Image (cartoon, rainbow, N blue to C red):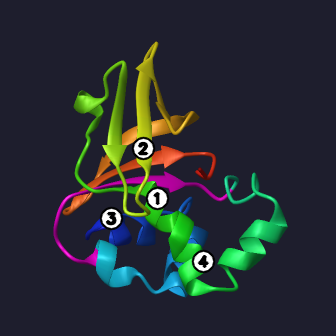
Amino acid sequence: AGMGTVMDVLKGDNRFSMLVAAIQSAGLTETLNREGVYTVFAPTNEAFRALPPREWSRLLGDAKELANILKYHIGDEILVSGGIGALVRLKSLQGDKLEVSLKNNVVSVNKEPVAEPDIMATNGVVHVITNVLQA
């Protein structure tokens, strides 16, 4: 039912179901399956639809290629809904910044609007995005 970490939170949701399989193909389970602090901006299945098949066929074809972008969806510590201010930048795993902003009750990350912030896991927090994130 999603009782676990940022990994299991996705494992137990129908909208993140195919996401799990990508993370799986990436084999970075231990990253998000271990305890710590993380902020995972989780792209839904229609978000997988918002990317050119070429770039994605690269990710699903190569684990570290997939992991490359997938790690950028994950912040280095927990930035919950109550921490979302005007614009707060949080670090990520890929190495760049998550551009989180709150404008008129609408949360945005990396210039992409969030659908539902603050789905907590045991090792961090998850935020539903309907688009995938790229630098």
Mark 3 and mark 1 in contact? Answer it, CB < 8 Å.
no
Q: Residue furthest top?
A: 104
Q: Return the disc, 4 or 1, that comes first in the chain's sequence.
A: 4
Write the residue at 28% across / 77% down: 33
In the displayed structure, would residue 1 be above or below residue 29? above
In the displayed structure, would residue 54 be above or below residue 21? above
User: In this figure, which residue is indicated by the disc labeled 3?
Assistant: 6
From the viewer's perspective, is the residue at label 2 or at label 3 nearer?
2
Tag shown at residue 65:
4
Q: Residue furthest front?
A: 95
Q: Tell me the magenta residue range.
A: 33-45
Quadrant hosting residue 52:
bottom right
User: In this figure, which residue is indicated by the disc labeled 2?
Assistant: 98
Q: Which is nearer the eye, 114 or 2?
A: 114
Q: Return the disc, 3 or 4, that comes first in the chain's sequence.
A: 3
17 falls in the magenta region = no
Amino acid at the residue labelled 1: Tyr
From the viewer's perspective, is the residue at label 3 or at label 1 nearer?
1
Write the residue at 17% across / 71% down: 35
Q: Return the disc, 2 or 3, that comes first in the chain's sequence.
A: 3
Q: Secondary structure at mark 3?
A: helix
User: In this figure, which residue is indicated by the disc labeled 1?
Assistant: 72
Mark 2 and mark 3 in contact? Answer it, CB < 8 Å.
no
38 falls in the magenta region = yes
Crowding near pointer 4: few (<14 within 10 Å), some, many (20+)?
Answer: some
